[PDB]
Length: 126
Length: 126
Ligand SMILES: [Mg+2]
Ligand SMILES: [Mg+2]
Image 1 (cartoon, rainbow over the protein chains, first blue to last red):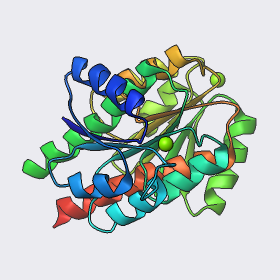
Image 2: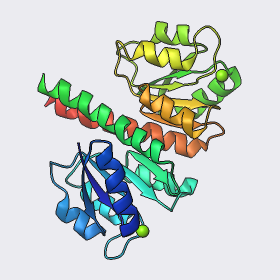
Image 3: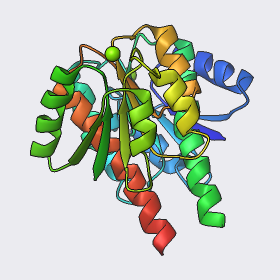
Image 4: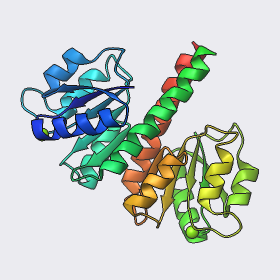
């Protein structure tokens, strides 16, 4: 499973890339919404997407990517109010996990969404 | 979209049934895990599942239903610690929302999972 990490915090993306690679995932990193849209293709199984970023924020990135891709999206951001969470889900995200987050919960939420994607893929191939 | 509500709190299930029917859903209620397994068939689009219940708890209900059904499951329970959340996701739930919860976030999470189910169904039919 290939994960596209989108966040301008280079300390967080380096830490998450190491954590997720140790959990068996292939991780690629984008540091803004424009770079995310450049790297998004059919090889991506899931996006971890921040909101506040320079060049193109995560809400605009989510709206743009949903015009061409149904790729699973988890918002992962310091914008964690109940209003922010509903906004992210309604604009096309599958899940929304505020920062600070628990590493184990993030890994379990990634695994839960990819388990459902795999079930859909098995049925489609059959 | 047809929702199976599983919780022993009759005050909560009556309130949620009214809320969800006003949001356009068809809602059926089970008050324990045994009744949930009796009511679970291919017509159910999503389960809202509690943990602490008499006769059969939600963790055992989730394990049993995952042997025959890939139906989307959201755990909705007062067992809200980070450890409880990871446990629920790892045992087969798609999402996990602790009580007390925000009504709008619950509705958005239901809508997000059913939006993904609809995308899978469209592809499968094509
Ligand atoms: Mg940021
Ligand atoms: Mg209960």
